[PDB]
Amino acid sequence: VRRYPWWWPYLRR
C-alpha cells in the first residue's frame, strides 16, 4: 500500500 493500486502491492509491494 505504498501508493499504487490496492492490488498492486501483491504485484510487487
Image: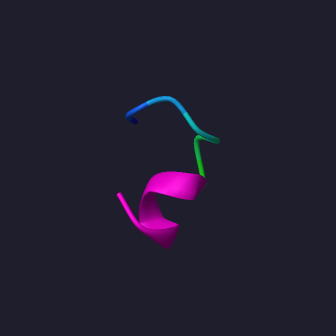
Q: Residue furthest top?
A: 3
Overall secondary structure of the magenta section: helix
Q: Residue at x 40, y 36 (%)?
A: 1
Q: Is 9 within the magenta?
A: yes
Q: Residue at x 44, y 54 (%)?
A: 9
Tell me how many marks there are.
0
Left or right of residue 13, residue 8 in this image: right
- The magenta segment: 8-13
Please say if 5 is above or below 12: above
Q: Position of residue 8 (x, y in %)?
A: 57, 55
> Quarter-wise, where is residue 12 in the image?
bottom left
Please say if 12 is above or below 2: below
Q: Quadrant of the C terminus?
A: bottom left
Left or right of residue 8, residue 12 in this image: left
The coloring applied to the image is rainbow
Please say if 6 is above or below 8: above
Q: Residue at x 50, y 29 (%)?
A: 3
Left or right of residue 11, residue 2 in this image: left
Please say if 11 is above or below 3: below
Q: Residue at x 58, y 41 (%)?
A: 6
